[PDB]
Amino acid sequence: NKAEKQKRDLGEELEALKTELEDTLDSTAAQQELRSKREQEVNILKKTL
Amino acid sequence: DQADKASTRLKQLKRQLEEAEEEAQRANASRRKLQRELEDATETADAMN
Amino acid sequence: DQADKASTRLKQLKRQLEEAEEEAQRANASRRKLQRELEDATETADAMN
Image 1 (cartoon, rainbow over the protein chains, first blue to last red):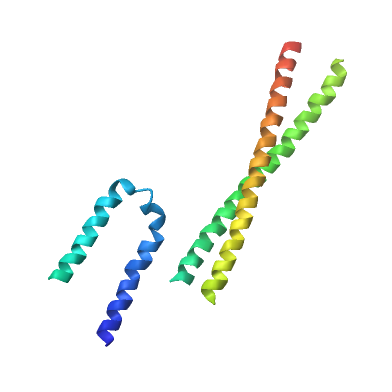
Image 2 (cartoon, each protein chain N blue to C red):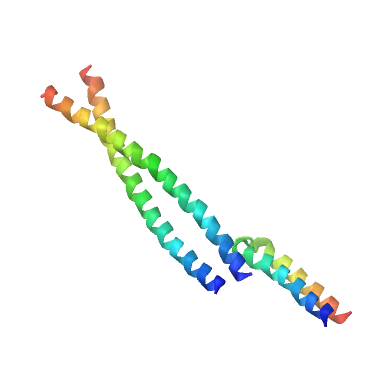
């Protein structure tokens, strides 16, 4: 239970940095589309693995 | 995270507001100095007539 | 409560920044007309010399 709690807490750190950088993600749409697709592919690999 | 993110943005607005207020002093001070020069031109125009 | 209080104070700063920007635009606009009038007086002074 403590391990799962730490995993959720660590995940919040990634979301905090993403929200603070959302103002620049819209301006960088030239490469954010390709980078965003790569992130989803990594998540699918973890779920499939 | 919202409080820290909101607090961080509030601090950024504080420095931005101070920068705008500081620039207003130079612009306001320059406006007063320009008014003094304009008064000399108006007085000189009377002597020119 | 800290996020709501910080968010409320953050929105209040936006009103001052928006109003401060209008003062700079109006103040800067006055300098344009002041410099324009002073430029005409400078040419008249040179011609009189």
